[PDB]
Amino acid sequence: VTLKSRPENLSFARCLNTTEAKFWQTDFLKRHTFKLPLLITDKAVLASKGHEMPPDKLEKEIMDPNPQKSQSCTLSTECDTLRIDFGIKVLPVKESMYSCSDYNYRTAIYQKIDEYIAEDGFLTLAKRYVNNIANARFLWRNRKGAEIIETIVTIEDKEYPSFNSKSFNLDTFVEDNATINEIAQQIADTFAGKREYLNIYVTCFVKIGCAMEVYPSQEMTFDDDDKGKKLFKFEGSAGMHSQKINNALRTIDTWYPDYTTYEFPIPVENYGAARSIGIPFRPDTKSFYKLIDRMILKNEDLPIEDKHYVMAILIRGGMFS
Amino acid sequence: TLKSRPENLSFARCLNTTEAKFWQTDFLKRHTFKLPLLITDKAVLASKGHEMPPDKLEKEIMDPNPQKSQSCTLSTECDTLRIDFGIKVLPVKESMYSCSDYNYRTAIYQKIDEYIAEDGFLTLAKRYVNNIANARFLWRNRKGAEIIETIVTIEDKEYPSFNSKSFNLDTFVEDNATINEIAQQIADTFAGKREYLNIYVTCFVKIGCAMEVYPSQEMTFDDDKGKKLFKFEGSAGMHSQKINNALRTIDTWYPDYTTYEFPIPVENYGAARSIGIPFRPDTKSFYKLIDRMILKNEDLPIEDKHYVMAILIRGGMFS
């Protein structure tokens, strides 16, 4: 019954499956009675070369500015508030292992998930996920200027008490409010297998102003030149990628080694990598690729912070041997 | 202890300018009248104006070709263009889109609150909304006008009016009440004392009855090869980058200023597309001045400090 290695095919599925985040434009005094479409507009930009260059060909850079047809979005000279609608389906973690070659590791992972299910049943992580819902980080750069950010979180035809998103800071997580705890309790239940699915529809109103600029999710252009800001279009309207929304709702890792010195949550990844900051925050030790080999292959009791991490990457998936 | 600039370094814009919409009114009733300014398609026969030897001249100098050129003209009953554009001023310390080294992050934040100490972005904001005040966002429509009257709105509080002809384009003024008060509001919405501010400027220009007014053009691919103008909600429009580059004309610290005496868009190398050749090519560019302000922890003159921070409102890339 001893465990030697990790399976050749060890693949978890997403237990937090988000839809795309479809954009709409509305007025804030009549948000509940308004829903105008937000369309991607097309604009010509002229190449302002701001990259570094020695004083050899800067005159050639200023001589021939090649224009680029960039897709950018302005709302309307009438609307005043972004309406994001996006859905999330939370599925039980146990019924998400997409492949496990060995069966002994499978029953070891099922016993280990149940061990966590007994002590803190996915309530800490759920509260943190719904705290990531609450502060409205869905808006990555759209959040940068607003007066009221209001997120309504509908759970199965039950419109919950609406959230103020600027009162909740980006760097601290709240365990007190009643709505966040009961929504997190439903998500904790869904994680269990006590409930087999939960559809959560979240609508965010951000009042950036009148005729201001939105910032949708960019898309990779075709490789045969045509370099320009091609934004995402979902149903003849702007939208954000479910990968951005999941990375927004995956920034729950405060239990990283260099915390007391950086004091900023990073998004959950296999070696603790933040692409905008650099210097991977969880290298060597505190890395699933050693922690679950210390938890399943060997058999000690990790502390609850590393236990919080090591089963928080299990909503994400993608491993191997 | 720092070594070089990070592989990822990106500053966002602290002046999110809006694409300006265009209306037609009459100066007599500029506040009780607002009609849309449509785009009209018109015909051109382009005669070639490229230098050609006399031998090949006859071949085309008498052979025209049809092109469709969109042009914009005011109605006979209106004599005033209304340019409505908003500005979102956001804090500079929060404009760091990416910093791939954290020591660079700490040192650049130390530079921000060192400048905020000496000057609360007062001179820069004075220059920016004086550039709002002198109606430089009218890029060429300013050229013939009776009275250019620009009026500003902050946070649903009206603001006093502005006679743009009284401000010359080469010298900046720091002695009126409204420029100083609005610049103080832009100044502390940049320092971080307040998270955001929205600016709504409408400009009334008296260009004349049935005169024609010139919005920003777009590039046509090889495809009509004709002037195509910006259309915004079925109305004439102006590019956001046009207004931002007009308002960025705050640089009076380029080395050869006592020989040219004119503001140039703020730019990494000083490569203004007007006069061509870059005005800060070697020693006063971005990529030497911040290669010294942060990495060499060396003190820079207040003017150079103004320039590198004006770029930090505008942009800034990595190695």
Image: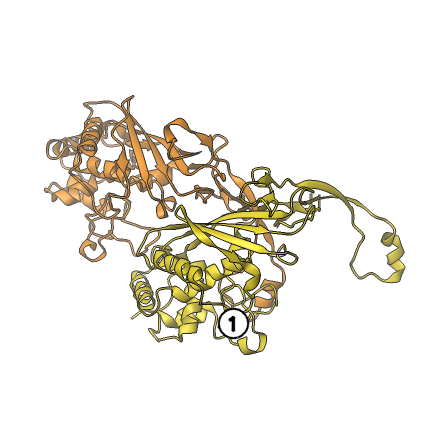
Chain colours: A orange, B yellow
Secondary structure under badge 1? loop
The x and y percentages for residue A111 are 14, 31
Q: The residue under label 1 is which amino acid type?
A: Arg
* Left or right: where B243 falls relative to A274: right
Q: Is residue B316 visible?
A: no
Q: Which residue is mark 1?
A: B280
- Give coordinates of residue B270: x percent, y percent: 52, 67
Is the residue A288 above or below the residue B318 in the image? above
Foreground pick, A31 / A90: A31
Q: Is A188 placed above or below A305 here?
A: above
Question: At x 40% / y 45%, what residue is drawn?
Answer: B156
For disc 1, the chain is B
The residue at 60%/48% (across/down) is B27
A26 or A48: nearer the eye? A26
Q: Is residue B8 above or below residue B79?
A: below
**Image location of residue A191, percent across then percent down:** 21, 29
Count of numbered tags: 1
* Residue A240 x %, y %: 41, 38
